[PDB]
Image: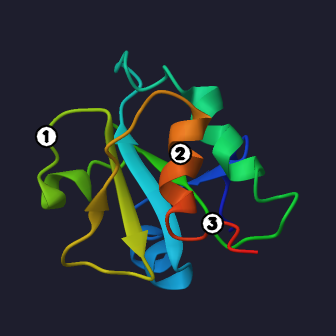
Amino acid sequence: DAPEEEDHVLVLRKSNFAEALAAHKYLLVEFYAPWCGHCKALAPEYAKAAGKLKAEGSEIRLAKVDATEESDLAQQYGVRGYPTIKFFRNGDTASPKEYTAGREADDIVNWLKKRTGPAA
C-alpha cells in the first residue's frame, strides 16, 4: 500500500529493505525489539535528527526495524543483540557501516554531518 513512517523516520521490512537501500543513497536503519530496553533511550533523539533536514531539504533519512516483527533481515545479517544500528549507502549489501554513537539526536546528525556538513 504505502511506506509507513514513525514520528520523523521510516520503518523497514523484508520488502522495503532491498528498496529503501537502493532507493535512497543515505539511509539509516536499526534492528530492535518491543521487549528491548536500550532501544528507546533515544526514541525522540533518533527522530529529531530526521527533522533537522525538513528545514533544509537534504536527502538523508533514518529508519528502524522490529526484529520481532520481521526477523527476516536480522537473521541473515547475523545481528549481535539490540539495539543494532546500521547505515546503508545507496544499497550496499556487502560492507555497510556501523553507528558508533547512541546517546541523543546530536550523535545522529554528527555522524550524518560527516557526509553532508555545511561546507558553505
Q: Give neighbour class at mark 1: few <14, some 14-19, many 20+ (Cα, 10 Å).
A: few
Question: Is residue 12 in view?
Answer: no
Q: Residue at coordinates 31% horizontally, 44% vertically from top-left?
A: 100
Q: Secondary structure at mark 1?
A: loop
The total number of labels drawn is 3
Q: Residue at coordinates 51% horizontally, 39% vertically from top-left?
A: 107
Residue 76 vs residue 39, the one in the foreground: 39
Q: Residue at coordinates 53% horizontally, 49% vertically from top-left?
A: 110
Q: Quadrant of residue 35?
A: top left
Q: Residue at coordinates 59% horizontally, 38% vertically from top-left?
A: 106
Write down the residue under mark 3: 117
Q: Secondary structure at mark 2?
A: helix
Q: Earlier in the sequence, mark 2 or mark 1?
A: 1
Residue 118 vs residue 7, the one in the foreground: 118
Q: Secondary structure at mark 3?
A: loop
Q: Quadrant of residue 13?
A: bottom left
Q: Amino acid at mark 1?
A: Arg
Q: Earlier in the sequence, mark 1 or mark 3?
A: 1
Q: Which mark is residue 108?
A: 2
Write down the residue under mark 1: 80
Q: Amino acid at mark 2?
A: Ile
Quadrant housing the C terminus:
bottom right
Q: Give neighbour class at mark 2: few <14, some 14-19, many 20+ (Cα, 10 Å).
A: many
Residue 103 higher or lower than 91, as above or below: above
Residue 94 higher or lower than 6, as above or below: below
Question: Is residue 101 in view?
Answer: yes
| Tag in front: 2 or 3 | 3
Q: Which mark is residue 93?
A: none
Q: Earlier in the sequence, mark 2 or mark 3?
A: 2
Q: Residue 88 location in percent, x, y?
A: 39, 69
Mark pair 2, 1: CA separation? 21 Å
